[PDB]
Amino acid sequence: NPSVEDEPLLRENPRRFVVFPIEYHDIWQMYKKAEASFWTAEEVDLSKDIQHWEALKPDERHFISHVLAFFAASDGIVNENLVERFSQEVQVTEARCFYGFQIAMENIHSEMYSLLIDTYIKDPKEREYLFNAIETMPCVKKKADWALRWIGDKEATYGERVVAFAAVEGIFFSGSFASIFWLKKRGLMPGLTFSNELISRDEGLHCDFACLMFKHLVHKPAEQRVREIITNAVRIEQEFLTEALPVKLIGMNCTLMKQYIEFVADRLMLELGFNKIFRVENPFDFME
Amino acid sequence: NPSVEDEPLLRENPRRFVVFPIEYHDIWQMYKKAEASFWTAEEVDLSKDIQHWEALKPDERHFISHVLAFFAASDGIVNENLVERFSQEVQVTEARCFYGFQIAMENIHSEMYSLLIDTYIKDPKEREYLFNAIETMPCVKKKADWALRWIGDKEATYGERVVAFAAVEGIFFSGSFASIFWLKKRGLMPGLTFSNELISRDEGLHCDFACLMFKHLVHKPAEQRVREIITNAVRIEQEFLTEALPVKLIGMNCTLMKQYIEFVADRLMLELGFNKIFRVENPFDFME
Ligand SMILES: [Fe+3]
Ligand SMILES: [Fe+3]
Image (cartoon, rainbow over all chains, first blue to last red; front, side, top):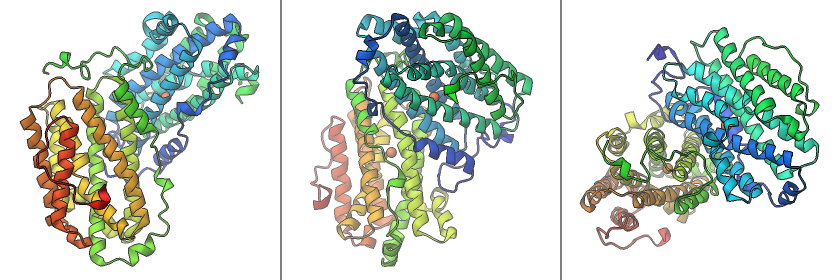
């Protein structure tokens, strides 16, 4: 261990776990905002959607199917990290609440996606292929592997891993969410899009929380280190969206995608308290 | 480590964390029942209650105040254990869902109680005394200490600790819940009782889940070991309810209390698959 004695969030010292003397109001209120957005997979009517899945072009189906599987697996990764690391490391109560609520929510997202997949792909053969994306889908490896390094990185700091998970939930998902909102614009798959609105909003909040934790950190990574972790993730997201699973497939412009990722990165950088990196405008009218 | 390779729930092997191929339907459905009972402290109108607190005899207030504080602290203990042990140890997904939902719920119970306390005890001086029951209230030490041993008991098995936590949530809370339902019968403190109905129902479910996990265990403690852990807890509960914080205080018969604890213990024993221990009838008409 380092200088954890110096970190308020980490100093192995609440000597607490009695919840009402509320010390951190900014953290609390985030939990409250979480708690208030609760929802269940059950609240999403997937009943029309099979028709739509039907009236879709193949390319549109390959795309979607792959994204669903990419999200299915990623949520899994997110949760594991929270479970075995974040929620263990952080000592401040308010933060424990938020992370415990986030885990419950990841599980619900995991279920929603599973349902989408099961509802669209009647062929259990496929089903499996997709459930096992980490071991099947190369298009999801890098990303999965990048994120997995951080869980196993036992030499690095919380400040570093917090930034990384914020890149995972906010950068690794950005393109995909955006692609889904694209479909909505085009009037397709209501169930897929309606859920997407819920999920994306949860993830946003999960990103804001991470930036807040970052703020409560004393010893954080140097601004160069942060740029590099962000940058690395941006690149990886761009590649997935234009090469591995090109947005062309649902009629999107790969170039504007690439630029939105960057816009997304710069917003995060600002939330973390740094200058922007790329200085690009948001290209999607609808993502505003 | 033992023979974890042999335990389905523990064998460090889901090689999973992809949630939809559902293996354990009994576990799943418990999670679903949990998920469906969600509620927030906010849903409880504590608005009339100050009057009641008023129209109460002192003895009734001492009692209640102490119980609230005892519950406030215990919930804290429950959660810590889940957080740092149960949810880490158990590998089966369905179980991870249930435990992650349980933690979110403990946190909400922790908040409800805090609120009760804050709503009844205007004197922040007191407030504190109660928030710090573990270090102040001797009437809550033994119990707290008994439960804490299990979190730190690093030589004992999951089978043993699961039984113990089931004794904590089901035995250590039984009397108290019962005392609160007694007040309801007598028409007093609606807010305290209404919440109590919610909480008690959650705890019940948390007990049933533990019995289910016990069932999925291969290598469990010998029936004598289980009797002894249960027995130990029964005794301790009886003592708290008749000596430390006597139910006389709210006009209850200490003798019938003692017998209900035992009735409560035997029900748990049966749920765990063993014979009853005490063979007493349930003495409370209203707890039926
Ligand atoms: Fe998430
Ligand atoms: Fe509980």
